[PDB]
Length: 338
Length: 20
Ligand SMILES: CCn1c(-c2nonc2N)nc2cnc(Br)cc21
Image (cartoon, rainbow over all chains, first blue to last red; front, side, top):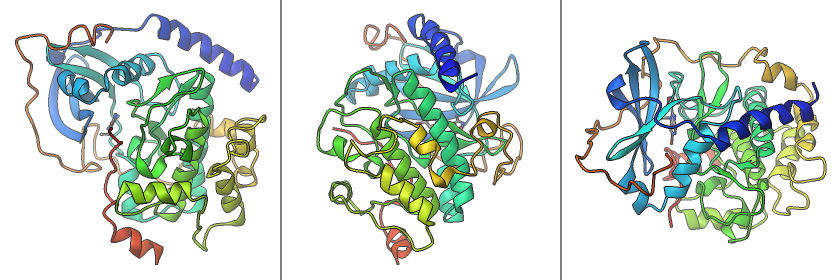
């Protein structure tokens, strides 16, 4: 079928789940706690084993009271409502969700391959075909998300897991939002912020296309296009309208990046009349077989070492903390729909 | 080099989302 036809069917499936979300599909007592995989202001992600199946999953745990203090109630409700409704090869699968007196739980597909971030920092950088393979997956994922009126808002290597086949899975939907018009929230990661966010303007899906430019640059250079010791110095660089490329970047890559890292919204690729096709049809993607990528028929440039379904050697170690459940319900009204 | 400057910077580890 045509891309328009495929996206229409994808919208029909998404809307049915978006309008009637799955709720309370498991319980904490159904999982065995193994190890902490990651932490942040959002809470933590724990490797767990579902006893009834023996399957391993990545359990994202948020403390309701802490979410409230961080003013992330609406953003957390967005995350879960969107995750339970989407279906795309390069999006992490939300297997179950539930809450208790203290916490919110999102049980996700576990990717033992770990974060792109770890591999990128260790290796140093990815060659252009390696970076292109990952970039093609993001282009397709954003075409899918944007067609559903979803804005992603936190693209970065920290948020991209590598599966057992070397393909990537977008995981973090903490700032994702379903919005038809413009939006105004100051959110994201300093290095990845589009100028219109820094400048407190109403912005749209074009911020994700700018973030794609930052990701491609970081993957291919080994460092981001705008970096400094403090966020303020990063913002000054972003808004300056200037970008420098490593001498090893191909002419095609520099041209694509100048069109993505474009301060002018009337000129930013992804944001023109031709939409995503300006990106897909760029010289840098001439060797990309978009269908073969979607169908996962392309041989991956890198396969993470497989050491078991529950091995954590591709993850850093974190201090292990108790999962406390109060005897009293906290923030019941705020998270009623979760 | 730009690489040396990045490696010596305080932002080579996992980067946190912003808060207001
Ligand atoms: C620890 C890395 N991680 C994972 C996963 N880590 O391993 N499999 C995953 N899935 N899912 C996340 C969702 N939100 C965040 Br925020 C981080 C996540």
